[PDB]
Image (spheres, rainbow, N blue to C red):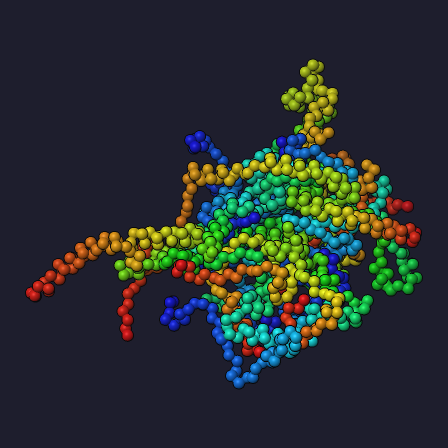
Amino acid sequence: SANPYKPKSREVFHPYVPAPEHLPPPAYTTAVLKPMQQFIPKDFYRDMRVDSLRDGVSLGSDFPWNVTHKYRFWRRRKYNVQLDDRFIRLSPVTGVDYYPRLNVFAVQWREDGQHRIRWFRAAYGLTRAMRAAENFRKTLEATGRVDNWRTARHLRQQMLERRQQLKLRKKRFAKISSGQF
Amino acid sequence: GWSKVVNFLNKGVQRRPHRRLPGQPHHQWNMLKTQLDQLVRSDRLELTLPRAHELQQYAEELVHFAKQNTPESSLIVESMIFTPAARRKLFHELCPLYANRPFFYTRVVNQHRLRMRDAAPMAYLEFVDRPGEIRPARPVGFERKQAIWEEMQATRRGRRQWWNHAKKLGLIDEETGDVISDINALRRPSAAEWEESDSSPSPYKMVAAPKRALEPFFVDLPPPTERYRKQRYVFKRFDP
Amino acid sequence: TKHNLTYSGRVRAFKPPSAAQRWEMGESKYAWRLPIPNLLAGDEMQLNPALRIDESTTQMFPDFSKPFFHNAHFNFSWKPEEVPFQQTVKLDITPWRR
Amino acid sequence: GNFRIKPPGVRHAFPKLGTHRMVMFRRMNLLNWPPEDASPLHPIEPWGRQFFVFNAFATIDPADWCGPRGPFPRLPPLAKPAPDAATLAASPSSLLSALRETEERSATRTVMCVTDFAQRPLMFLGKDDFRALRENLPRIKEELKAFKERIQPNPVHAQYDLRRKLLVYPRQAMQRLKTGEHGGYGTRRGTIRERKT
Amino acid sequence: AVPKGKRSKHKCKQRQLIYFFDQFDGVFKRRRESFYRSFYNPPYFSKQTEQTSLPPSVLRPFRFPGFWPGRFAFKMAS
Amino acid sequence: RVNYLLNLLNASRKKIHEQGGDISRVYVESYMLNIQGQIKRPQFRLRMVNLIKTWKFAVVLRFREYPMDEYFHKLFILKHVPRSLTTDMRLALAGQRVGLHAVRDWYPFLDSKT
Amino acid sequence: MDHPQFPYEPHELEKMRDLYGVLLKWPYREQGQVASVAARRASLESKREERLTEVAGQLKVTTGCSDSYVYAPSEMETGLYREH
Amino acid sequence: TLYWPPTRKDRSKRIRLPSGKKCFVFNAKRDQDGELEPVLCFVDSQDNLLMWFNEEELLEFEKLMPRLESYYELWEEKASRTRMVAAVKE
Amino acid sequence: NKVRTDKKERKRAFPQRGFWKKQNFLQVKNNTVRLAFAVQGVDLLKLKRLRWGEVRKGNTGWWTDDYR
Amino acid sequence: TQDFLLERHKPLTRDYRYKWKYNFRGRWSRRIGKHKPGIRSVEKKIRQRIVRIRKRYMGQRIEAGLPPYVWGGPWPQWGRKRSLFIRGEMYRRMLIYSF
């Protein structure tokens, strides 16, 4: 559910992790890196390459592979491959969602204040069901059955039946507005 | 149960043209195709009598359509078969072997014994005219002509009994009214032979052998049926 | 059978990393190129790891400019510089918004 | 696949996970194959056929051959018999080795073997056959080019489209999700609730 | 529904005989006939019993020597 | 479970042959069944616990070696011939393991019509 | 080459269902003859636009003979991670 | 007419190698799906199939061929030395 | 369990048509054992298949008998 | 087209013996997979068979020892979560804690 307690941003957070506040400068800071006068202490690279990840910004040009040491994932890494960016069950059309337990693509919208949903069974084919859902959503938008996407023409056309219903209501409660009863 | 109930419940019932195997139709079709592939690869399968009777028709269909050699029949055979080994065996051995056989390329033999474990009647289903066949295949084509000619010459009864068929076959000489003398005159090239339009001292010359040419050297490898093997059944232990 | 079998109901053998595989007191993967090890080797030992490659297990070298697996011949947890620049793909979690 | 028989260590030093598991389960049947003195196997694309060169065992002269026997006829190798029981008993060798002694063969016939991806042999060629193929190569390329032009696309691809265009194609119903007391009407409605705060 | 009384020994014997004839004529006669017809072929040799079975054979013995008019064994060679 | 009876029959035939009886004229004259008991096992069901039984029985068979006169009167006069013997005769004739005289020799016992 | 990518376009699904026993032995075909892969390729190309001899690879030689190499620090205490 | 053995026009002129083996070109039902494709076929002295090479396979084989000559030479020398050992050891 | 304190005998009082054989898992285990033996030069499967009193040295059998 | 409609034709293959409309799950049948009662789709079946073919080919190349090449084309995204980068951040934090 779209809770009020989820975080605002959906990004992957890399917080700044400060060291215990009273530790002195680490060992690798004693290194002298002048080309004419060199001293590289013990564990210089080991300490410094981990200290560099502290700020949470300079994560490394190869992140997260520069911190992933387990060979389980390196054994799976591929090179010179082109990858997609979108989960196959996500539609760019607003209001289209997937219910996996039912195996349906749902279109949810609002029409005259009411919240309405329609199902499109995916057993006939995932692509067919998703495209049917998108087409239904776009048809609703075009015909003006989605409130937020309506146009001035749609509003004008709907106002006629709104007026008819309002006149019926006025005749229903005529005896009160006149001062009788 | 009671045996007479079979008669009672089959009074007024038709035999099913196809014997139905367990599972749904797609599973049944897959099973039949798999066993047809295995039958092609092995030349003979020990099955239950009903299963042999059921798979025989698909074996016959496979051979019949493989012989025709058209794209349509090739696609039919492809829809029937699964494995490249079965495809190769069929096209390169069975089709030349049956080139002159019009039909009826298989046989079913009832073993007349019940399987020990479940008392299932048993049978063999085998392609005909292959080495190791249960009984010898009868000849077709010019070989059949020669067999009938020999039978006609063996005895007068054979001549009388094949007289009319011999006329159609061309074994009767119209000039003299007797059987022809040189049956070899009726020899004609067959599809199984290599057309000769293409028209010994080497240290590695291949040696002649009944089935395949042999190399003039030895390689320490068992035959293909013995090269790779595994236990037929690993025992599953009872858990009390 | 040695340790190629477990003599119990254990199905998957667990073994901790070996001393040579550890870092401290472990075998450096570039020490075979150093002077002292080569001075001690003499003619008794050859330190080049290329000589211990199992021909029946390793694959042929691929072209680095074309799609290939990392596990074939690298056997370490880093990317060689000779492999060209790789594309970092970040998931598009809200396509509907754009 | 040329294991190291009686190797050092207490565990297999070769991969045994994934396809390698079945690779080793296959190669363990033929410890003697490929031959010990064989050249390095060289594979080629795309199906992974392999070539290698080795000296095979000489066979008896066919004139002396007793003939074919069994489902797989073969020429017996030319082998020197193993020492007799009396000789072995007199020798200082242990009973184990004495029992394990076998015949001696002569690996003196150079030949190339072509195998599939799994090292299963397909064909053996001598130097003369190899050189004849090499000489005839140029014409083979022309023949391949000529026979390529005979290729025609399969007709089922067009026939299926034609039948789809012209014939009746039923599409049965699927996934008839069932209801309980409350029936279905093609659409759903979300309830309206006022805040109780 | 349950029986209203115990079936008697007389009727149980009758049922024994009836079921014997049913099973006989439905299963046993047929199985015996098939068994005796199978004798005209060499006995089945299971390849999974090679490790312990006898070598394959085709001969079927003549089991009543008192009705055999031929020779029973050949004289020892020399 | 008929392997038990088959084992009994095979062992009895072997024993009689070893003792010197003529297997060819040994008949099963009678049988006797003697109960020994039944092992009971619980069978747990919806509303009750039942006891399923496995029987334990013994079988006594009476074999008799017919004297030669009785054997003659049975096989030759009354034509009550063992089907095993007749099948062996027919197999011998079919396989040509005996001479042509065997047909008339075995005519009194060969087939139903003969 | 390419082979059909799930989810399949309805025509592809439908054809493969009808010709299961023929088209699913070797589904590899040249680029462009598979609609499922072609559509994904085209979408990726459009997104790229919106955003805007074969030789075996070898690791460079790491051995040497010169004094500069022989008498260089071993750097085993330093924590070098890119061992090679 | 049958697909195998290929008829006159369905195959090229057969090359007879100096061991009784022949090789020719024709369109074979490839193992993957059975669709026709031109291959260099191989048969023994009794006209039994051994195997065939695709165009790409044949080009790679040609690429590797010169090295197999050197392998032939080296293993011929090895066989000669084994023969010498046998002769010395009677 | 081995001490027969469980209630697993209750189901065995009812018939069942068959039981799974776990042949994939059992064959993987068996082949692991076979590989462990074979890397040291032992043909466990051949030994298991040998007839009583049968001696076969190396990878030999009926085919060796046929061709020798 | 009229000639076709007038002529009687025959099936292209034998695949009609599958009778796919009878590949179904009953209302009370045990749940094998995520198939609802009624006719079952074949998308997953086809995907699994193609996976088997691809795996066979790649394993064959591994056994042969051919170079470790892969198909380079568009790999579809089957998951939603950025597990790689989230786990990398976790590892970064663990390394900092050890330091």
Along the line of sight, the residue nearer the viewer: J32 or H48: H48
Q: Name which residue lies at 64% across and 60% down.
A: C72
Q: Identify whether J65 is placed above or below B138.
A: below
Along the line of sight, the residue nearer the viewer: C69 or D107: C69
Does residue B224 show up? no
Q: Identify whether C62 is placed above or below G78.
A: above
Q: Name which residue lies at 60% across and 73% down.
A: I3
Quarter of the figure that contains the C terminus of chain A: bottom left
Along the line of sight, the residue nearer the viewer: D119 or B108: D119
Q: In this view, does H73 lie to the left or right of A43?
A: right
Q: Position of residue D32 (x, y in %)?
A: 76, 55
Q: In this view, does F5 lie to the left or right of B208?
A: left
Does residue C22 show up? yes
Q: In this view, does A31 lie to the left or right of E51?
A: left
Quarter of the figure that contains the N terminus of chain A: bottom left
Q: Name which residue lies at 64% across and 50% down.
A: G53
Q: Where is residue F39 in the image (x, y as percent from the top left)?
A: 58, 66
Q: Position of residue D59 (x, y in %)?
A: 83, 46
